[PDB]
Image (tube, coloured by chain):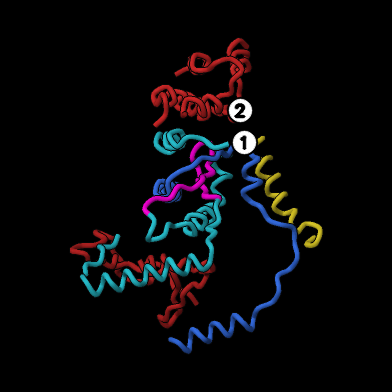
Amino acid sequence: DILASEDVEGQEAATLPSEGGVRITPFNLQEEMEEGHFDADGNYFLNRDAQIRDSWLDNIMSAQALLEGLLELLLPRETVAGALRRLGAQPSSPQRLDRLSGLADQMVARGNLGVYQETRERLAMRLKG
Amino acid sequence: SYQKLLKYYVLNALKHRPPKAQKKRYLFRSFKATKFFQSTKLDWVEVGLQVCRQGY
Amino acid sequence: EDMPPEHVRKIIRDHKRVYLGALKYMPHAVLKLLENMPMPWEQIRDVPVLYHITGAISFVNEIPWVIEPVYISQWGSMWIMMRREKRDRFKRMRFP
Amino acid sequence: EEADAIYAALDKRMDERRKERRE
């Protein structure tokens, strides 16, 4: 046998959860009927489906502009990563290396993968077509 | 504490068995051939900060 | 070959299936970081680093090889110097 | 599509160490 929510004679609403750090019981048997259930004599039986057991929970610019900037920062027949190697060789030019890395990361973030092993001529053909 | 450490040493000595023959194992050599990874030289503290912020 | 540190520093500083697949090997990178912590008698240590194109993960890629009697002699010198320091001088550091 | 194929090839290469003995 199981009791319904109508044979409780005097449930009320849940005004406030806590005050002063003390948790307030919401005066209704809704959460006890969600966790377990009652018999005819008023005992309690609890659900026991806790497989994972959760031991912490238990206790609580445009791309064309990018290509123009890269073709500006490259010499012919040179890769982008090789340009990083040369301009990083404190380096000789920190600011142009910073600009080259920034343009490379803005090209990587748009989905273009593998831009480091790319010569100047293939990027020029990409800007043309 | 001496007796328990000696207990662990006797257990590790008794449970020892020779390792099984297999192909030699290189994770970073297969990571290096991928174009998505690059190699550099960094200080230990900088890469120690990079690892923990990437984990965060 | 290798690459200058400023590039990967900019990588980590300015910051998805290519980003998602590289995050599987995080405790392996944690192990490679923890097995190469520098010795007390070293001031700095420069190690190689494997890293992803977007800075998803950073590896260490070095095995801490030492010569055994040199290593034991160095830790014995540490033992002597720390006995010397406690018989001469304590304030423990404040954790985290 | 390419990146998942590359990581799947690296997974198969890591599985190659014990492939003919395990299956």
Do tags 2 and 1 sit on the same chain? no
Image quarter for residue C9?
top left
Residue at 49% across / 59% down in the picture?
A: C35
Residue at 49% across / 42% down in the picture?
A: B41
Chain drawn in cyan: C
Q: Is A15 placed left or right of A60 in the picture?
A: left
Look at the image and say whether residue C45 sits in the magenta stretch: yes
Q: Is A129 placed left or right of A24 in the picture?
A: right
Residue A6 visible here: no
Pick the front one: D9 or C81: C81
Magenta residues?
A: C43-61
Task: Return the x and y of residue D2 as percentages of the image width and height.
Answer: 66, 35
Answer few, some or many: residues within 10 Å of disc 1's Cα (few below 14, many 20 plus, some between 14 and 19): some
Q: Which residue is mark 1?
A: B35
The answer to whether marks 2 and 1 mark residues whose Cβ atoms lie closer than 8 Å is: yes
Vertical arrangement, residue A20 with respect to residue A113, above or below: below
Task: Return the x and y of residue D19 as percentages of the image width and height.
Answer: 77, 57
Pick the front one: A30 or A69: A69
Inspect the image, locate mark 1, and give the three-letter code of the amino acid beneath it.
Lys
Give the colour in which the image draws chain B.
blue
